[PDB]
Image (cartoon, coloured by chain):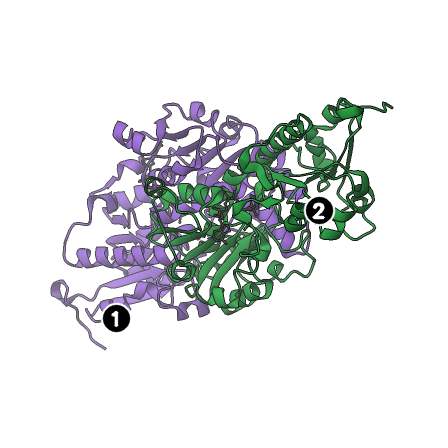
Chain colours: A green, B purple
Amino acid sequence: AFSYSSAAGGESKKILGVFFAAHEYAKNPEFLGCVENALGIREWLESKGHKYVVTSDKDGPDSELDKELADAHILITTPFHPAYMTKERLAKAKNLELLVTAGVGSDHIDLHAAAEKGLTVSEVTGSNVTSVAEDEVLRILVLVRNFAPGWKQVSEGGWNVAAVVHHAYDLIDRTVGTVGGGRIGQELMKRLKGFGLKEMLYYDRNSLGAEREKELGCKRETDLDTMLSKCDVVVVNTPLTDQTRGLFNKERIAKMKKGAYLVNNARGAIADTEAVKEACESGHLGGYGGDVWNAQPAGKDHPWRYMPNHAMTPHISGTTLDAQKRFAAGTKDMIDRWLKHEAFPEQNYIVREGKLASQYL
Amino acid sequence: AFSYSSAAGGESKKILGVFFAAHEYAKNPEFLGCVENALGIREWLESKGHKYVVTSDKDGPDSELDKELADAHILITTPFHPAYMTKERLAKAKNLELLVTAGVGSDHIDLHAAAEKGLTVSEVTGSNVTSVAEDEVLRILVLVRNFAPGWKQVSEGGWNVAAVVHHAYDLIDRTVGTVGGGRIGQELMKRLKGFGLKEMLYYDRNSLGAEREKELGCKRETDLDTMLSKCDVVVVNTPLTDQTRGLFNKERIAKMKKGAYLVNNARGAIADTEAVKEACESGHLGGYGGDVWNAQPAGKDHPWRYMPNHAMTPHISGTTLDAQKRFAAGTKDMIDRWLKHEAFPEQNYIVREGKLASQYL
Ligand SMILES: NC(=O)c1ccc[n+]([C@@H]2O[C@H](COP(=O)([O-])OP(=O)(O)OC[C@H]3O[C@@H](n4cnc5c(N)ncnc54)[C@H](O)[C@@H]3O)[C@@H](O)[C@H]2O)c1
Ligand SMILES: NC(=O)c1ccc[n+]([C@@H]2O[C@H](COP(=O)([O-])OP(=O)(O)OC[C@H]3O[C@@H](n4cnc5c(N)ncnc54)[C@H](O)[C@@H]3O)[C@@H](O)[C@H]2O)c1
């Protein structure tokens, strides 16, 4: 009922948010990361005379996302329920100036297309990198120690120790490799310190400190194939870039030790769907697990749901209640800064001044 | 077909082993811990002119265990499929001199009764204490991060991030308490080092080093109730003694923080069955998980199978293929030493010279 705002010329800005529905779970106000509570920023936007419109309806061209997209200045996405911003969707977005990811990973945006339009793309760098590091250890131990079939077995009334431990091992004196030595890569190695690994290995374009490598008890592998062929466990910790799409194909998976484990809480598309299914069926992989899929939601018939020895979940690790707090705060901050014509922290920029952040090249 | 042995007077000794069946999984000879492969010691016993008899049939009084028990000199048990050696069963065991546990925890033996008969009870101290420490971290992360419902959800074709993360948290800046600062207690704290806990706490009759406490980043809690009321997560790491039976009752569970997590890979009976079920149903417990049950096998109707927020499996953690190697070797060694009238390592003795090891008092 108020026509103006505290912005230039009192132009009312429209902020569009796409979040999953929490339905009854939204009764917990700590549950910020959902369409119902919308990061708890509605009153703070409405009180500036700005418009705040949110939806969980992002799929197909009849979507609330496509309706509302035309006159939106600011788009908030979340990786857990990601608005896929194609060249077409960006081109219809006539007022769009800022794309902010409530989480980490902005690959659900056409970054090359956003860059060409001079749009700004940002994410809450660092906000759930500890949460994913914890979940990666979870997935390693669950696959190595064969937890899931055992939990299934006793929940359905059975008792057969052998049907579980015929495929259960200890992590001690095994070799773990992280593809990526970024924030999550490093938080993983910090958390694998006490497990008495043979070696902790990382592959990245960037050497860490010699001092950092000592701190993390890790060693750099120059060649990826050289790292993979030493590893009992492989963890994916890169963004989804043009370099990293389908990086874990037939060829690259056969380069891994027989019965080795593949954990991916980075992005599904970094691992070829059919290649992971088959190597799980053959046993060339001891198992595959992660919260991330090449389509979000994953179609009912995504094979990663039904393949053997999998530790799959929906996209949960970076959106625990504790993670939601951090990326909510970071999202509000960047919208605050944008309205104040203030630079974001340099690390939060994925696309700025028509250029992609070096880690997406 | 040979009537004598390399023992005193060439008395053929009978070694009785009770193991679970591995059926087809016994095709893997690394799968030592099963009735079919029987720790791979048959030829080494038979070649000394000793008798080796093994069975998975240990339950009821019509059992192969009860038939064979009468004339057995040496009994090998395993906690994963434990022969319950009651006062009655011991009294029928006319030749029995040595009870050796292929694993750790000999509570499935009436130790007070074994002590009265002057029998020797031993276990492979240290043999799977790293394996259980790993699995305890597994169970903590699985319960805190709510893995299991998510794995169930996607395996049955669903997709609902909220139905999982409404009860999913991060471990960082939370407080973990281990009831027991023994081998597993210590291997747990070593593995929780990198998780940025608020505090790592332990309760034990025995202080560790001041130097050890620094090494483990831990602090001692004198009063159990004082430890419990600070703890987001509680891990059970004591043997099942007279002190520790039903230690986790109604009263003691209500002393834990609301929505706190209880992990038990020690022994089921340390936690009252109904008390754990109810506190899981009320949410006073965020969840309960472990591989150990007060009856082994657990009856089809054990409530811990069907209660909410559980991370239960059969008894697997201390009998991964890697653990089986270590307790097989230790069992063969102690039988070797017994035949040579050689003392076992002091730590392997549960019952010696009519006395119980201090940690079972
Ligand atoms: N499951 C979740 O909820 C969740 C949450 C957080 C992040 N993620 C995913 O994890 C990714 C990693 O996050 P982060 O915080 O570690 O980011 P980061 O930018 O700190 O780390 C990424 C690392 O990858 C390296 N890299 C990029 N392309 C490479 C290539 N071709 N070869 C070698 N190294 C390459 C970079 O040098 C960098 O060190 C995110 O981009 C996101 O896709 C998922
Ligand atoms: N799930 C499995 O497969 C598996 C495998 C290994 C052991 N376990 C169980 O774990 C138990 C612990 O194993 P461990 O290797 O740490 O043994 P440990 O003897 O090194 O540690 C036990 C600790 O409990 C303490 N303790 C005993 N009674 C106590 C009491 N009333 N109050 C306070 N402290 C008390 C002792 O002081 C000791 O430090 C075993 O007895 C066994 O029951 C299970």
Looking at the image, the residue that sits furthest to the left is B9
- Secondary-structure class at tag 2: loop
Q: Which quadrant contains ligand 2?
A: top left
Where is residue B48 drawn, in percent x and y? 19, 69
Compared across the picture, whether A2 is left or right of A128 comes to right
The one of A64 and A242 positioned closer to us in this rendering? A242
| Badge 2 amino acid | Ala
The one of B208 and B41 positioned closer to us in this rendering? B208
Label 2, on which residue? A83
- Which residue does the image show at 59% across and 32% down from the upper left? A344
Compared across the picture, whether B91 is left or right of A88 comes to left
Label 1, on which residue? B43
Where is residue A218 drawn, in percent x and y? 35, 47
State the quadrant of the C terminus of chain B.
Answer: top left
Question: Given the image, what chain letter belongs to the residue carrying mark 1?
Answer: B
Among the 4 quarters of the image, the one containing residue A79: top right
Where is residue A210 drawn, in percent x and y? 33, 43
| Badge 1 amino acid | Glu
Question: Given the image, what chain letter belongs to the residue carrying mark 2?
Answer: A
Compared across the picture, whether B274 is left or right of A168 comes to right
Does residue A33 lie above or below A92 as drawn? Answer: above
For disc 2, the neighbor class at 10 Å (few under 14, some 14 to 19, many from 20) is many
Total number of numbered discs in the rendering? 2
- Which residue does the image show at 80% across and 28% down from the upper left? A12
